Length: 116
Ligand SMILES: Cc1cc(N2CCOCC2)cc2[nH]c(-c3c(NC[C@@H](O)c4cccc(Cl)c4)cc[nH]c3=O)nc12
Image (cartoon, rainbow, N blue to C red):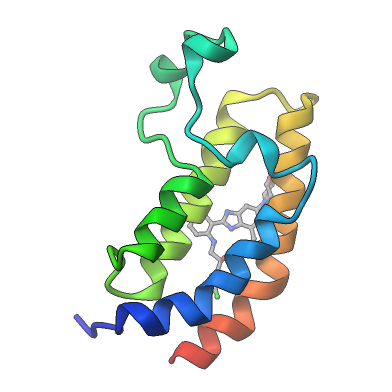
C-alpha cells in the first residue's frame, strides 16, 4: 500500500539493472523477449507461462509501472526462474542465468535497504 515515487524507483533501481545488462555474454539471452519461432524453440510457451526479460522490466521502470520496489524484485526472479525451468542444467543459458542471479543477490540488498 505504501507507494514510491516512480522517479525515486528509477534512480535507486536503475544501477542494479545496469549491473545485469553489463554482463556480457551472460545478459544477451535476457535483453529482449524470448521469441520462440525466431530462435527455433517453439515449445517455449508450453513451458514458460509468464515470460519476462530485461527490456520489459526496464520499460516498467522507465514508465513508472511499479508501485513499490519488491515488484521489481518479483519480475527479476521470475525472469531467472523462467530460464532455469526451460534450459537444462548443462546449457549455457542456464549457467548465464546463474551468473546474472549471483550479480543480483550481491547488489540488491543495500539498495532495498536504502529505499526503506
Ligand atoms: C538467492 C537465491 C538463490 C537461488 N539458487 C540458484 C539457482 O539454482 C539453485 C538455487 C534461487 C533463488 N530464488 C530466489 C527468489 C527470490 N528471492 C528474494 C531475495 O532476492 C531477497 C529476499 C529478501 C530481501 C531481499 Cl533484498 C532479497 C524471490 C522470489 N522468488 C525467488 O525464487 N532467490 C534465490
